Length: 489
Ligand SMILES: [Mg+2]
Image (cartoon, rainbow, N blue to C red):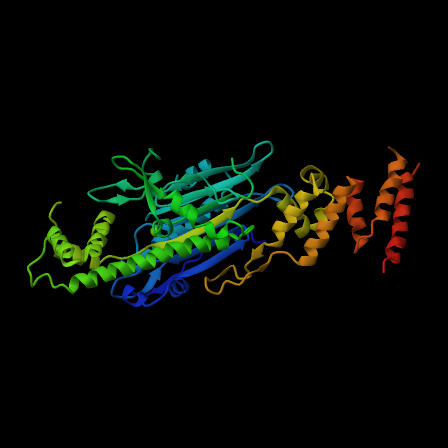
Protein backbone atom coordinates (compact mmCIF):
# COMPACT_ATOMS: atom_id res chain seq x y z
CA UNK A 1 0.00 0.00 0.00
CA UNK A 2 1.77 3.12 1.30
CA UNK A 3 5.24 1.58 1.20
CA UNK A 4 7.05 4.12 -1.02
CA UNK A 5 6.91 7.91 -0.66
CA UNK A 6 9.01 10.51 -2.50
CA UNK A 7 8.72 14.30 -2.30
CA UNK A 8 7.73 16.28 -5.37
CA UNK A 9 9.25 19.25 -7.19
CA UNK A 10 7.85 22.28 -5.34
CA UNK A 11 8.13 25.93 -6.39
CA UNK A 12 7.13 28.65 -3.93
CA UNK A 13 6.74 32.43 -4.01
CA UNK A 14 9.48 33.55 -1.61
CA UNK A 15 9.00 37.08 -0.29
CA UNK A 16 11.76 39.37 0.93
CA UNK A 17 12.94 39.83 4.51
CA UNK A 18 11.58 43.40 4.55
CA UNK A 19 8.13 41.84 4.09
CA UNK A 20 8.81 38.80 6.31
CA UNK A 21 9.85 41.00 9.26
CA UNK A 22 6.18 41.91 9.82
CA UNK A 23 5.23 38.21 10.01
CA UNK A 24 5.41 35.74 12.88
CA UNK A 25 6.72 32.17 12.71
CA UNK A 26 3.27 30.77 11.90
CA UNK A 27 2.93 32.99 8.83
CA UNK A 28 6.47 32.17 7.67
CA UNK A 29 6.10 28.40 8.02
CA UNK A 30 2.69 28.17 6.35
CA UNK A 31 3.92 30.08 3.28
CA UNK A 32 7.18 28.16 2.79
CA UNK A 33 6.79 24.53 3.89
CA UNK A 34 4.83 21.35 3.18
CA UNK A 35 4.26 18.10 5.07
CA UNK A 36 4.62 14.61 3.57
CA UNK A 37 3.48 11.92 6.01
CA UNK A 38 3.93 8.16 5.58
CA UNK A 39 2.68 6.83 8.93
CA UNK A 40 2.86 7.54 12.65
CA UNK A 41 6.49 6.35 12.59
CA UNK A 42 7.65 8.28 9.50
CA UNK A 43 6.99 11.76 8.13
CA UNK A 44 8.77 14.34 5.97
CA UNK A 45 8.68 18.15 6.07
CA UNK A 46 10.09 19.95 3.02
CA UNK A 47 10.33 23.64 2.27
CA UNK A 48 12.59 26.56 1.48
CA UNK A 49 14.04 29.16 3.84
CA UNK A 50 15.72 30.85 0.86
CA UNK A 51 14.90 34.55 0.60
CA UNK A 52 16.36 37.85 -0.56
CA UNK A 53 16.76 41.06 1.40
CA UNK A 54 14.85 43.65 -0.66
CA UNK A 55 13.22 41.66 -3.48
CA UNK A 56 10.96 38.64 -3.91
CA UNK A 57 11.92 35.32 -5.49
CA UNK A 58 8.84 34.60 -7.61
CA UNK A 59 9.99 31.11 -8.74
CA UNK A 60 11.95 29.63 -5.83
CA UNK A 61 12.55 25.98 -6.70
CA UNK A 62 12.96 23.50 -3.83
CA UNK A 63 16.03 21.49 -4.84
CA UNK A 64 15.78 18.99 -1.96
CA UNK A 65 14.27 15.51 -2.19
CA UNK A 66 13.50 12.98 0.55
CA UNK A 67 12.27 9.42 0.12
CA UNK A 68 11.42 6.27 2.04
CA UNK A 69 10.80 2.63 1.10
CA UNK A 70 9.48 0.24 3.76
CA UNK A 71 10.55 -3.37 3.23
CA UNK A 72 8.81 -6.52 4.46
CA UNK A 73 9.89 -10.08 5.23
CA UNK A 74 8.67 -13.20 3.43
CA UNK A 75 5.24 -13.21 5.10
CA UNK A 76 4.50 -9.52 4.44
CA UNK A 77 5.46 -8.20 7.89
CA UNK A 78 7.55 -5.03 8.08
CA UNK A 79 11.16 -5.87 8.95
CA UNK A 80 13.04 -2.82 7.69
CA UNK A 81 13.09 0.22 5.45
CA UNK A 82 15.35 2.40 3.31
CA UNK A 83 15.40 6.20 3.64
CA UNK A 84 17.29 8.77 1.56
CA UNK A 85 17.35 12.57 1.37
CA UNK A 86 19.24 14.90 -0.98
CA UNK A 87 20.19 18.58 -1.08
CA UNK A 88 20.60 20.23 -4.47
CA UNK A 89 24.07 21.79 -4.61
CA UNK A 90 24.13 25.30 -6.04
CA UNK A 91 21.26 26.54 -8.16
CA UNK A 92 18.87 29.38 -7.46
CA UNK A 93 21.08 31.86 -9.33
CA UNK A 94 18.24 32.73 -11.74
CA UNK A 95 18.72 29.99 -14.35
CA UNK A 96 15.57 27.87 -14.10
CA UNK A 97 16.85 25.22 -16.51
CA UNK A 98 19.81 24.91 -14.14
CA UNK A 99 17.42 24.44 -11.21
CA UNK A 100 15.52 21.78 -13.16
CA UNK A 101 18.77 20.03 -14.06
CA UNK A 102 19.99 20.05 -10.45
CA UNK A 103 16.66 18.75 -9.15
CA UNK A 104 16.66 16.08 -11.88
CA UNK A 105 19.82 14.50 -10.45
CA UNK A 106 18.73 15.17 -6.86
CA UNK A 107 15.38 13.41 -7.33
CA UNK A 108 16.81 10.57 -9.44
CA UNK A 109 19.63 9.90 -6.96
CA UNK A 110 17.14 9.50 -4.10
CA UNK A 111 14.79 7.39 -6.22
CA UNK A 112 17.52 5.10 -7.56
CA UNK A 113 18.82 4.44 -4.04
CA UNK A 114 15.34 3.47 -2.82
CA UNK A 115 14.48 1.15 -5.73
CA UNK A 116 17.70 -0.84 -5.24
CA UNK A 117 17.61 -4.11 -3.29
CA UNK A 118 21.29 -4.54 -2.37
CA UNK A 119 23.04 -3.37 0.79
CA UNK A 120 23.94 0.29 1.25
CA UNK A 121 27.58 -0.17 0.20
CA UNK A 122 26.73 -2.04 -3.01
CA UNK A 123 23.77 0.23 -3.84
CA UNK A 124 26.01 3.30 -3.81
CA UNK A 125 28.70 1.52 -5.83
CA UNK A 126 26.22 0.76 -8.63
CA UNK A 127 24.62 4.20 -8.89
CA UNK A 128 28.00 6.00 -8.93
CA UNK A 129 29.48 3.63 -11.56
CA UNK A 130 25.35 18.68 -11.86
CA UNK A 131 25.93 17.89 -8.17
CA UNK A 132 23.72 16.97 -5.23
CA UNK A 133 24.61 15.95 -1.68
CA UNK A 134 22.84 12.95 -0.18
CA UNK A 135 22.22 11.26 3.17
CA UNK A 136 20.69 7.79 3.42
CA UNK A 137 20.43 4.73 5.65
CA UNK A 138 19.00 1.20 5.62
CA UNK A 139 17.73 -0.68 8.68
CA UNK A 140 16.68 -4.33 8.59
CA UNK A 141 15.97 -7.11 11.08
CA UNK A 142 18.29 -10.14 11.37
CA UNK A 143 17.41 -13.42 13.17
CA UNK A 144 19.87 -13.38 16.06
CA UNK A 145 21.14 -9.81 15.68
CA UNK A 146 17.92 -7.78 15.53
CA UNK A 147 17.79 -4.45 13.73
CA UNK A 148 20.96 -3.72 11.74
CA UNK A 149 21.27 -0.22 10.33
CA UNK A 150 23.94 0.75 7.82
CA UNK A 151 24.35 4.48 7.22
CA UNK A 152 25.76 6.75 4.51
CA UNK A 153 26.20 10.54 4.38
CA UNK A 154 27.84 12.75 1.75
CA UNK A 155 27.90 16.54 1.91
CA UNK A 156 25.78 18.89 4.03
CA UNK A 157 23.51 16.03 5.13
CA UNK A 158 23.17 15.16 8.81
CA UNK A 159 21.85 12.09 10.64
CA UNK A 160 20.91 11.91 14.33
CA UNK A 161 20.02 8.57 15.95
CA UNK A 162 18.02 8.72 19.19
CA UNK A 163 16.31 6.08 21.32
CA UNK A 164 12.77 5.82 22.71
CA UNK A 165 13.51 8.52 25.33
CA UNK A 166 14.88 11.13 22.86
CA UNK A 167 18.40 10.39 24.16
CA UNK A 168 21.13 10.88 21.56
CA UNK A 169 23.13 7.75 20.71
CA UNK A 170 24.91 8.40 17.40
CA UNK A 171 25.47 11.20 14.90
CA UNK A 172 26.60 11.08 11.27
CA UNK A 173 28.13 14.50 10.60
CA UNK A 174 28.28 16.64 7.47
CA UNK A 175 31.37 17.50 5.44
CA UNK A 176 32.92 20.52 3.73
CA UNK A 177 35.79 20.48 1.22
CA UNK A 178 38.22 23.41 1.11
CA UNK A 179 38.57 24.27 -2.58
CA UNK A 180 40.03 27.74 -2.04
CA UNK A 181 40.20 30.79 0.20
CA UNK A 182 36.96 30.52 2.15
CA UNK A 183 35.62 28.01 -0.38
CA UNK A 184 34.15 25.28 1.83
CA UNK A 185 31.83 23.23 -0.39
CA UNK A 186 30.20 19.96 0.70
CA UNK A 187 31.22 16.82 -1.22
CA UNK A 188 28.73 15.34 -3.66
CA UNK A 189 27.57 11.87 -4.63
CA UNK A 190 28.75 12.59 -8.18
CA UNK A 191 32.28 13.12 -6.82
CA UNK A 192 32.43 9.43 -5.85
CA UNK A 193 33.01 8.50 -9.50
CA UNK A 194 35.67 11.21 -9.88
CA UNK A 195 37.83 10.09 -6.93
CA UNK A 196 38.83 6.76 -5.43
CA UNK A 197 39.21 8.44 -2.02
CA UNK A 198 35.58 8.11 -0.96
CA UNK A 199 36.46 9.73 2.39
CA UNK A 200 22.71 -2.39 15.69
CA UNK A 201 19.44 -0.51 16.20
CA UNK A 202 16.68 -1.07 18.75
CA UNK A 203 12.91 -0.74 18.84
CA UNK A 204 11.43 2.72 19.29
CA UNK A 205 14.66 4.43 18.22
CA UNK A 206 14.33 7.75 16.40
CA UNK A 207 16.43 8.35 13.28
CA UNK A 208 16.31 11.99 12.16
CA UNK A 209 17.81 13.16 8.86
CA UNK A 210 17.97 16.86 7.99
CA UNK A 211 19.39 19.22 5.38
CA UNK A 212 21.66 22.26 5.58
CA UNK A 213 18.59 24.48 5.90
CA UNK A 214 17.47 22.64 9.05
CA UNK A 215 20.43 21.81 11.29
CA UNK A 216 22.37 24.80 9.96
CA UNK A 217 19.82 27.02 11.72
CA UNK A 218 20.33 25.35 15.12
CA UNK A 219 23.35 25.74 17.39
CA UNK A 220 26.26 24.28 15.44
CA UNK A 221 29.34 22.36 16.57
CA UNK A 222 32.50 22.07 14.45
CA UNK A 223 33.35 18.43 15.15
CA UNK A 224 36.53 18.11 13.08
CA UNK A 225 38.65 20.33 10.84
CA UNK A 226 41.59 19.08 8.79
CA UNK A 227 43.36 20.96 6.00
CA UNK A 228 40.48 20.45 3.53
CA UNK A 229 37.80 18.52 5.48
CA UNK A 230 35.31 19.95 7.98
CA UNK A 231 33.04 17.64 9.98
CA UNK A 232 30.19 19.70 11.42
CA UNK A 233 27.13 18.86 13.50
CA UNK A 234 24.77 20.39 16.06
CA UNK A 235 25.28 21.08 19.76
CA UNK A 236 23.91 17.94 21.42
CA UNK A 237 22.97 19.87 24.57
CA UNK A 238 20.89 22.39 22.61
CA UNK A 239 19.36 19.72 20.36
CA UNK A 240 18.29 17.67 23.39
CA UNK A 241 16.35 20.53 25.02
CA UNK A 242 14.21 20.77 21.87
CA UNK A 243 12.53 17.55 23.07
CA UNK A 244 11.71 18.89 26.56
CA UNK A 245 8.10 19.50 25.46
CA UNK A 246 7.74 15.77 24.67
CA UNK A 247 9.16 14.00 27.75
CA UNK A 248 5.97 12.70 29.37
CA UNK A 249 3.85 12.50 26.20
CA UNK A 250 3.84 8.84 25.07
CA UNK A 251 4.50 7.83 21.45
CA UNK A 252 4.48 11.05 19.40
CA UNK A 253 4.16 10.90 15.63
CA UNK A 254 7.23 11.45 13.47
CA UNK A 255 5.44 14.50 12.05
CA UNK A 256 5.10 16.03 15.52
CA UNK A 257 8.81 15.43 16.12
CA UNK A 258 9.82 16.85 12.74
CA UNK A 259 7.44 19.76 13.37
CA UNK A 260 9.20 20.65 16.64
CA UNK A 261 12.68 20.61 15.10
CA UNK A 262 11.61 22.54 11.99
CA UNK A 263 9.77 25.14 14.08
CA UNK A 264 12.91 25.78 16.15
CA UNK A 265 15.11 25.93 13.04
CA UNK A 266 12.77 28.41 11.34
CA UNK A 267 12.41 30.38 14.58
CA UNK A 268 16.16 31.02 14.59
CA UNK A 269 16.05 31.55 10.81
CA UNK A 270 13.37 34.24 11.07
CA UNK A 271 15.20 36.00 13.92
CA UNK A 272 18.61 35.83 12.21
CA UNK A 273 17.28 37.53 9.07
CA UNK A 274 15.53 40.17 11.19
CA UNK A 275 18.76 40.89 13.08
CA UNK A 276 20.53 41.31 9.73
CA UNK A 277 18.08 43.93 8.45
CA UNK A 278 18.05 45.70 11.83
CA UNK A 279 21.85 45.84 11.61
CA UNK A 280 21.98 47.17 8.04
CA UNK A 281 19.27 49.75 8.77
CA UNK A 282 21.14 50.87 11.89
CA UNK A 283 24.36 51.25 9.89
CA UNK A 284 22.69 53.27 7.12
CA UNK A 285 21.19 55.58 9.77
CA UNK A 286 24.62 56.75 10.95
CA UNK A 287 25.79 58.07 7.54
CA UNK A 288 29.42 57.11 8.11
CA UNK A 289 30.46 59.13 5.04
CA UNK A 290 29.64 62.42 6.77
CA UNK A 291 32.20 61.56 9.46
CA UNK A 292 34.50 59.80 6.95
CA UNK A 293 34.43 56.24 8.40
CA UNK A 294 35.26 53.19 6.28
CA UNK A 295 37.51 50.82 8.29
CA UNK A 296 35.59 48.03 10.01
CA UNK A 297 37.69 48.49 13.16
CA UNK A 298 36.92 52.22 13.11
CA UNK A 299 33.22 51.44 12.68
CA UNK A 300 33.56 49.37 15.85
CA UNK A 301 35.24 52.41 17.41
CA UNK A 302 32.11 54.39 16.51
CA UNK A 303 29.52 51.87 17.72
CA UNK A 304 31.27 51.09 21.01
CA UNK A 305 31.77 54.80 21.76
CA UNK A 306 28.27 55.89 20.67
CA UNK A 307 26.58 53.35 22.95
CA UNK A 308 25.54 50.64 20.46
CA UNK A 309 27.76 48.04 22.10
CA UNK A 310 25.26 45.27 21.31
CA UNK A 311 25.05 46.42 17.69
CA UNK A 312 28.83 45.96 17.59
CA UNK A 313 28.76 42.40 18.95
CA UNK A 314 26.02 41.64 16.42
CA UNK A 315 28.42 42.78 13.69
CA UNK A 316 31.26 40.79 15.28
CA UNK A 317 29.17 37.61 15.40
CA UNK A 318 28.50 37.88 11.66
CA UNK A 319 32.20 38.51 10.98
CA UNK A 320 32.81 35.18 12.72
CA UNK A 321 29.90 33.61 10.82
CA UNK A 322 31.88 34.39 7.66
CA UNK A 323 42.34 43.11 13.72
CA UNK A 324 43.00 43.34 9.99
CA UNK A 325 41.51 46.26 8.08
CA UNK A 326 38.46 45.68 5.86
CA UNK A 327 36.45 48.59 4.39
CA UNK A 328 32.78 49.37 4.96
CA UNK A 329 31.66 49.52 1.31
CA UNK A 330 32.84 45.91 0.89
CA UNK A 331 30.94 44.42 3.84
CA UNK A 332 27.77 46.50 3.43
CA UNK A 333 27.40 45.67 -0.27
CA UNK A 334 28.21 42.04 0.58
CA UNK A 335 25.57 41.77 3.32
CA UNK A 336 23.05 43.59 1.11
CA UNK A 337 23.47 41.06 -1.72
CA UNK A 338 23.44 37.93 0.47
CA UNK A 339 20.76 35.26 0.16
CA UNK A 340 19.46 34.03 3.52
CA UNK A 341 18.61 30.37 4.03
CA UNK A 342 18.53 27.18 2.00
CA UNK A 343 16.05 24.51 0.98
CA UNK A 344 15.01 22.94 4.29
CA UNK A 345 13.92 19.31 4.50
CA UNK A 346 13.73 16.79 7.35
CA UNK A 347 12.58 13.19 7.77
CA UNK A 348 11.97 11.38 11.07
CA UNK A 349 11.90 7.57 11.16
CA UNK A 350 10.98 5.53 14.24
CA UNK A 351 12.20 1.93 14.41
CA UNK A 352 9.08 -0.24 14.85
CA UNK A 353 8.40 -2.91 17.44
CA UNK A 354 8.39 -6.53 16.27
CA UNK A 355 5.09 -7.31 17.99
CA UNK A 356 3.53 -4.07 16.73
CA UNK A 357 4.34 -5.02 13.13
CA UNK A 358 3.26 -8.64 13.64
CA UNK A 359 -0.11 -7.37 14.87
CA UNK A 360 -0.27 -4.76 12.10
CA UNK A 361 0.06 -7.36 9.35
CA UNK A 362 -2.27 -9.67 11.25
CA UNK A 363 -4.95 -6.96 11.08
CA UNK A 364 -4.31 -5.80 7.50
CA UNK A 365 -4.01 -9.30 6.03
CA UNK A 366 -6.31 -11.51 8.13
CA UNK A 367 -6.07 -14.53 5.82
CA UNK A 368 -2.49 -14.98 7.09
CA UNK A 369 -3.81 -15.73 10.59
CA UNK A 370 -2.82 -19.41 10.72
CA UNK A 371 0.52 -18.76 8.99
CA UNK A 372 1.80 -16.19 11.50
CA UNK A 373 0.02 -17.93 14.39
CA UNK A 374 3.09 -19.75 15.83
CA UNK A 375 4.96 -16.43 15.60
CA UNK A 376 2.67 -15.00 18.29
CA UNK A 377 3.64 -17.91 20.55
CA UNK A 378 7.25 -16.68 20.24
CA UNK A 379 6.87 -12.90 20.61
CA UNK A 380 3.99 -12.73 23.10
CA UNK A 381 5.31 -13.55 26.57
CA UNK A 382 2.82 -11.69 28.80
CA UNK A 383 -0.35 -9.62 28.57
CA UNK A 384 1.83 -6.56 29.23
CA UNK A 385 3.45 -7.12 25.83
CA UNK A 386 0.09 -7.11 24.04
CA UNK A 387 -1.30 -4.19 26.05
CA UNK A 388 1.84 -2.18 25.32
CA UNK A 389 1.60 -3.09 21.63
CA UNK A 390 -2.06 -2.13 21.21
CA UNK A 391 -1.56 0.99 23.35
CA UNK A 392 1.02 2.15 20.80
CA UNK A 393 -1.28 1.25 17.88
CA UNK A 394 -4.07 3.22 19.58
CA UNK A 395 -2.23 6.56 19.42
CA UNK A 396 -0.98 6.14 15.84
CA UNK A 397 -2.06 8.94 13.49
CA UNK A 398 -1.89 8.89 9.70
CA UNK A 399 -2.45 11.65 7.15
CA UNK A 400 -5.05 11.07 4.39
CA UNK A 401 -3.42 13.52 2.00
CA UNK A 402 0.14 12.22 1.69
CA UNK A 403 1.31 15.71 0.67
CA UNK A 404 -0.46 18.75 2.12
CA UNK A 405 0.44 22.25 3.36
CA UNK A 406 2.00 22.30 6.82
CA UNK A 407 -0.79 24.49 8.24
CA UNK A 408 -3.58 22.23 6.90
CA UNK A 409 -2.19 18.97 8.32
CA UNK A 410 -5.24 16.84 9.16
CA UNK A 411 -4.59 13.54 10.93
CA UNK A 412 -6.78 10.63 12.00
CA UNK A 413 -6.28 7.32 13.75
CA UNK A 414 -4.46 4.56 11.86
CA UNK A 415 -6.79 1.91 13.34
CA UNK A 416 -10.49 1.77 14.14
CA UNK A 417 -11.27 1.47 17.84
CA UNK A 418 -13.40 -1.67 17.46
CA UNK A 419 -10.76 -3.27 15.21
CA UNK A 420 -8.11 -2.79 17.91
CA UNK A 421 -10.22 -3.82 20.91
CA UNK A 422 -11.44 -7.06 19.33
CA UNK A 423 -8.07 -8.03 17.84
CA UNK A 424 -6.45 -7.42 21.24
CA UNK A 425 -8.97 -9.69 22.98
CA UNK A 426 -8.42 -12.42 20.37
CA UNK A 427 -4.64 -12.40 20.78
CA UNK A 428 -5.05 -12.07 24.56
CA UNK A 429 -7.28 -15.16 24.65
CA UNK A 430 -4.88 -17.00 22.33
CA UNK A 431 -2.05 -16.31 24.80
CA UNK A 432 -4.18 -17.34 27.79
CA UNK A 433 -4.71 -20.74 26.12
CA UNK A 434 -1.18 -21.47 24.91
CA UNK A 435 -2.15 -35.24 27.33
CA UNK A 436 -4.43 -36.78 24.70
CA UNK A 437 -8.22 -36.45 24.49
CA UNK A 438 -8.21 -35.08 28.05
CA UNK A 439 -6.69 -31.79 26.91
CA UNK A 440 -8.96 -31.96 23.86
CA UNK A 441 -11.85 -31.56 26.31
CA UNK A 442 -10.08 -28.94 28.46
CA UNK A 443 -9.83 -26.57 25.49
CA UNK A 444 -13.62 -26.64 25.18
CA UNK A 445 -13.83 -26.10 28.96
CA UNK A 446 -11.81 -22.88 29.03
CA UNK A 447 -13.74 -21.59 26.01
CA UNK A 448 -17.03 -22.51 27.69
CA UNK A 449 -16.30 -20.73 30.97
CA UNK A 450 -15.30 -17.69 28.91
CA UNK A 451 -18.03 -15.22 27.91
CA UNK A 452 -16.46 -12.84 25.37
CA UNK A 453 -18.57 -10.69 23.06
CA UNK A 454 -18.30 -11.49 19.35
CA UNK A 455 -17.11 -14.98 20.26
CA UNK A 456 -17.63 -16.02 16.62
CA UNK A 457 -13.86 -15.43 16.24
CA UNK A 458 -13.36 -18.81 17.94
CA UNK A 459 -13.13 -20.18 14.40
CA UNK A 460 -10.42 -17.56 13.92
CA UNK A 461 -8.75 -18.95 17.05
CA UNK A 462 -9.30 -22.61 16.13
CA UNK A 463 -7.29 -22.08 12.94
CA UNK A 464 -4.36 -20.86 15.04
CA UNK A 465 -4.97 -23.74 17.48
CA UNK A 466 -5.33 -26.54 14.91
CA UNK A 467 -1.85 -25.82 13.51
CA UNK A 468 -10.34 -42.66 17.25
CA UNK A 469 -11.56 -39.62 15.29
CA UNK A 470 -11.43 -37.61 18.51
CA UNK A 471 -10.74 -34.41 16.57
CA UNK A 472 -14.27 -34.81 15.19
CA UNK A 473 -15.70 -35.21 18.70
CA UNK A 474 -14.07 -31.96 19.87
CA UNK A 475 -15.18 -29.89 16.87
CA UNK A 476 -18.60 -31.41 17.48
CA UNK A 477 -18.40 -30.03 21.02
CA UNK A 478 -17.23 -26.76 19.46
CA UNK A 479 -20.48 -26.65 17.51
CA UNK A 480 -21.87 -27.01 21.03
CA UNK A 481 -20.16 -23.68 21.75
CA UNK A 482 -22.52 -22.36 19.07
CA UNK A 483 -25.27 -23.09 21.60
CA UNK A 484 -23.21 -21.06 24.07
CA UNK A 485 -23.16 -18.34 21.40
CA UNK A 486 -26.95 -18.62 21.08
CA UNK A 487 -27.23 -18.24 24.86
CA UNK A 488 -25.39 -14.91 24.57
CA UNK A 489 -27.98 -12.13 24.69
MG1 LIG B 1 20.71 23.01 0.99
